[PDB]
Image 1 (cartoon, rainbow, N blue to C red):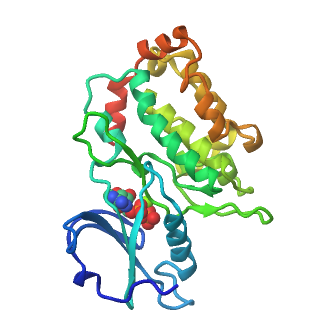
Image 2 (image 1 turned 90 degrees about the vertical axis):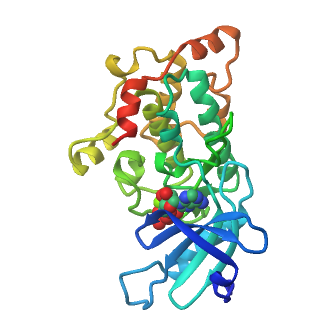
Image 3 (image 1 turned 180 degrees about the vertical axis):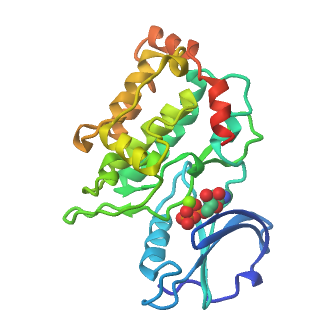
Length: 301
Ligand SMILES: Nc1ncnc2c1ncn2[C@@H]1O[C@H](COP(=O)(O)OP(=O)(O)O)[C@@H](O)[C@H]1O
Ligand SMILES: [Mg+2]
């Protein structure tokens, strides 16, 4: 693909650093023609097919091609792409409100009803992605951000499509990637991957959101890999004493070793914790609350 060959600085004024990836740095920028703010992701090109630094042409194209296709309120959009000798620069929708968990950590308390209002928007972004056969493959708290933390009902934006893949019916995909505490057993075990891995990671995010504890985290990476593979977790009372039974059921349906038996995105949206079937189930979710004291500790780590 020819991407834009002009200098990005002819069109944007860049500002403060937002974040960084292994071969990427993300900066805030302002488009000169509109005065509107975006995020510029500068990805270092590899340089020789022979080299070890930088991202391959294939991998940059895959990320661009996926973002280009997506148009949904809970996922970032791609605005423009530029290229020079050293970098491909993606101009992305800016997510200016930081990480969801940091915003929630600034609260006094959070009921499960309040928590599901945020979690439902994650589920809506992923439902959109899976309906297009896109696996995100790096769902974790740092990639769940807020468009604007100053509004009364902040909107979730899923970011970071650098590991995302369109599922190819017809070939198997296997690869090592992602953060050990947040990946599914099929990643841990180098088995065929699909849309199910995303579902497992949502189960981990939800477990943390309610408890402030990471369910599979060990003292070493090896122990974390071994806990994930064995599905070795529990809901210990210290952490989950105010958690509804519906919330444990939702998590248990996601934290399932066999991908074929795990809950899909369409079913997660119909689960009674998300969509209560009667007034009694709705009151259980309204009265139940997150373990805020432990949650704050987790968000400061
Ligand atoms: N659209 C965005 N808005 C605000 N911050 C962003 C945006 N995209 C990425 N970032 C920040 O930059 C970091 C690095 O970008 P990311 O896309 O995660 O790169 P990688 O694909 O290499 O992991 C993210 O973890 C986040 O902190
Ligand atoms: Mg990232």
